[PDB]
Length: 133
Ligand SMILES: Cc1cc(C(C)(C)C)c(O)c(C(C)(C)C)c1
Image (cartoon, rainbow, N blue to C red; front, side, top):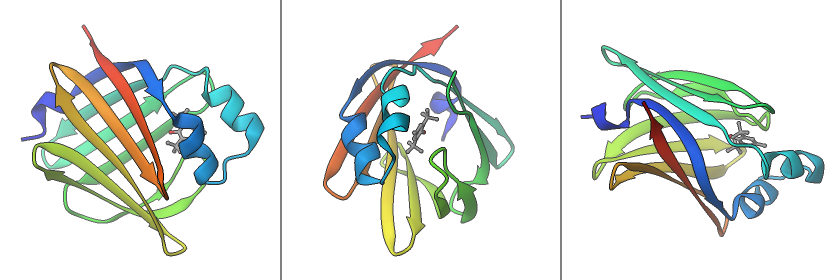
């Protein structure tokens, strides 16, 4: 059910990422470099385990998880969070919890593109990824 998310994806558009990062308390210098970074996201499965890599010139992250099972995560901005990823309405929904705060990272396939919507507080960022051959 996750299979159409799998593969290598490149960022092609971003809206409001600075607002999202600022809401999370990311410092201005980190925001500045992130506003110009074009990450590559790689999503692979092996049985019930998904691995999601985010690679860039700036920061790199990797998580592995089973859908519907909580995992500890250290985010790119060094937040220590409790995470869970679920499929909901065909969307891959990643919820992070820390210090009573929440943020959602929601991925949806629209016309073969991967739309990532990042919400924290009132900030809503939309990032568009396109598949690599
Ligand atoms: C500063 C910064 C913050 C984030 C989140 C806040 C989405 C975790 C992030 O994912 C990245 C890369 C996409 C560059 C890894 C950089």
